[PDB]
Amino acid sequence: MSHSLKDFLEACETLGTLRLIVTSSAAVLEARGKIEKLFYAELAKGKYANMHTEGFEFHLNMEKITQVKFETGEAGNFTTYAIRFLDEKQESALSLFLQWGKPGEYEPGQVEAWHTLKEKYGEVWEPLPVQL
Amino acid sequence: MSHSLKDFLEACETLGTLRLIVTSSAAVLEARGKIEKLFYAELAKGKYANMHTEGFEFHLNMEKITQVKFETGEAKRGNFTTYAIRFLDEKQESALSLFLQWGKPGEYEPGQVEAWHTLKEKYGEVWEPLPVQL
Ligand SMILES: [Zn+2]
Ligand SMILES: [Zn+2]
């Protein structure tokens, strides 16, 4: 399965509140927010998807993402729902988790929206070449 | 010279609102907030500095930082001066950058830039963490 990473990122707006996770060699930042109002720009280093919210800013070099995977886990006694954006080394450059309110209480239709994306794009898939 | 990374992170509370930047191989996340209410924990992979706010959670493996550098830069959009603290790993790559958070372009909080220079003078423009201890 091969799909547009741009289309997919925009489609993540349907997931409601997310926990966006980016990890370096030594740090982790886990930001709470909804994906929306994405803007794109091409630079020397890559073709970027970008977001500016009140609490945080986000940039994704779409050209470096080789595969996207859906994943569930266990937290409390409840299921977690994640989407991983993997790089050439098969390491997660970005992870998106559905964000609950009180522990395990997801937003109405949120878990459904996640399954809808997984069914539409597939369990694991590779992005098509990026064109801005 | 060498200093305690723990003491340094505690001292960062004096810098007011920061912009915490963590970069992976392909993504950048920037979160706005003061470095305050830090808590430490020893995990399997090492001693971590952490923060929990409503908007974000932050974790730093202190044992992986080999060098810390103060840098004044210039913003791409605005052409205004930026003030950063970069936490380098063993590859001399920034595992975390803390920027003074600007309001309007080049606008900082009262005493904030002076506080950055004071911290820089106290720790040095480039310094190395001591073996991590809480
Ligand atoms: Zn940015
Ligand atoms: Zn966390």
Image (spheres, coloured by chain):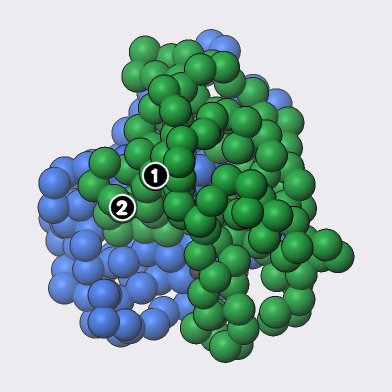
Chain colours: A blue, B green
Q: Nearer the viewer, residue A23 or B75?
A: B75
Tell me which numbered mark, 1 or 2, is placed earlier along the sequence: 1
- Measured as percent of width and height from the top left, residue B113 is found at 73, 65
For this orientation, the residue located farthest to the front is B1
Say which mark, if any, is on residue A98.
none
Residue at 74% across, 56% down: B115
In the rendered image, which quarter is residue B118 located in? bottom right
- Measured as percent of width and height from the top left, residue B126 is found at 45, 52
Query: Which class describes the residues within 10 Å of circle 1: few (<14), some (14-19), or many (20+)?
Result: many
Identify which amino acid the numbered label 1 is placed on: Gln
Q: Label 1 is found on which chain of the structure? A: B
Identify which amino acid the numbered label 2 is placed on: Glu
Query: Which class describes the residues within 10 Å of circle 2: few (<14), some (14-19), or many (20+)?
Result: some
Residue at 57% across, 88% down: B79
Q: Nearer the viewer, residue A11 or A30?
A: A30
Would you place residue A27 above or below residue B126 in this image?
above
Residue identifier under label 1: B67
Residue at 41% across, 79% down: A40
Q: Say which of marks 1 and 2 sits in front.
A: 1
- Measured as percent of width and height from the top left, residue A36 is found at 56, 65
Say whether residue A81 is left or right of residue A42: right
Say whether residue A46 is left or right of residue B1: left
Say which mark, if any, is on residue B93.
2
Element type where label 2 sits in the image: loop
